[PDB]
Length: 292
Ligand code: HEM
Ligand SMILES: N=C(N)C1CCCC1
Image 1 (cartoon, rainbow, N blue to C red):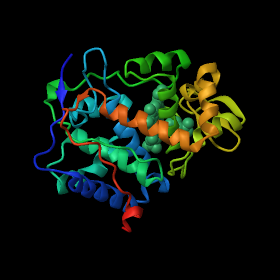
Image 2: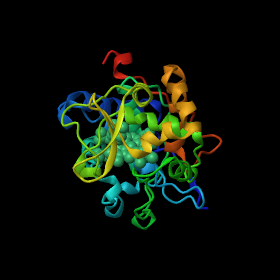
Image 3: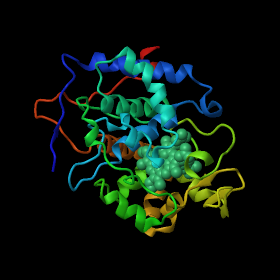
Image 4: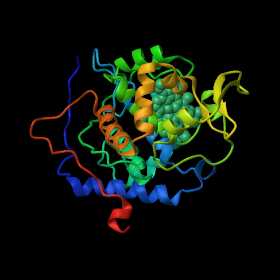
């Protein structure tokens, strides 16, 4: 019941944040080899989600505001295994722009990755403020993958997301891959998708899925094509309400982009109070738009 008021980094404006965006985007382009040539796009999206997804609407603990992923309890959350790669990517960015708060940097990294991967524009607001180590939420607030649609629906109520918002946000699972050592769910061994599209929904609907056990003895849904879905992914076509929305996004790229952009911004802003005279949300230009 904590109040976190957005406070703009002193004297900073749109141009300052576009510079940070640009530095992230340029490094995304440069460090192209990461994870068998997937690049750092997907892991930066996952990082922005995990630092936000600790939020609890009931007492306003967790959330992106405090930048608490920088503290050992949170960065060592078993749910966050692999995200150290995103944090290391952002380290030199933070060094170049030491004035940006940690929450702002982690959330901006997600926005930048989505846009640079040809996703929708995601309006972004500055003003998250680093909070002390004792404000770090405990482990166990991020969702399990081995569960069903009812679990997913209930889980996301804590983040104030409804069915449409849940289904839209899950479209980010078009990006990157599971890594057996991180999560107990499997390779492809090589490259995966690093372009932001509605392919998650198309694959759910069109692939011939088989329920198999992986080398970690966990069940996952696999296709002959070499794709996989988590049990929680597959639950979106098992539940009739989720299934309708899956079909909608599979058949309308623009609608998916618009809904994802709204839900992703909301996720990244949950728990933050923006003063009435705060700057309007910024919409950053991509490198391509800038001729960079
Ligand atoms: C029911 C909710 C969710 C569950 C159970 C879940 C679970 C997982 C798991 C187990 C992984 C694999 C981690 C690894 O092995 O490296 C993963 C990866 C990923 N997740 Fe989710 N996730 C959920 C929701 C979301 C949301 C809401 C987003 C963003 C909007 C997201 C973005 C990603 C991305 C981009 C990756 C790929 C990361 C990489 O390639 O390094 N996930 N997720
Ligand atoms: N369904 C998939 N292939 C996603 C890859 C990252 C988590 C799940």
